[PDB]
Length: 115
Image 1 (cartoon, one colour):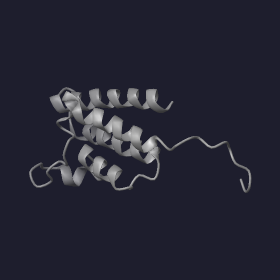
Image 2 (cartoon, rainbow, N blue to C red):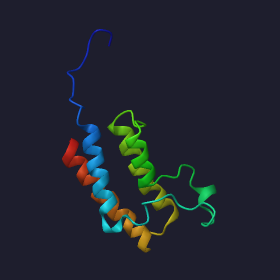
Image 3 (cartoon, rainbow, N blue to C red):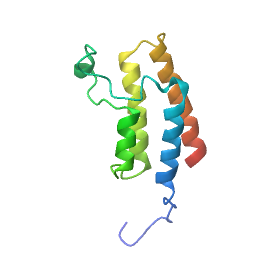
């Protein structure tokens, strides 16, 4: 509360470490469905159904231009990418499986890096 603060967590490396995690996600073989924004002209249903589209290129541009105020807002956009994928794709499809694999990959790096 006012003039009563918890001890300061060192957050000075967070930017660098989220960039590294994002590089590792970008270079995973199963990243291909997630590298670029879904083309809303060419994919029926996507625009109406997926209210907040997100992809790795968009996260990378946000990261590089100071649009994440902290590491939790970064993790929210990454998870959004997988949550969108589960909303639109059957679990037993190539893209559906890619999305489960990538989420697992991400969550491990996240835990090992920060928790």
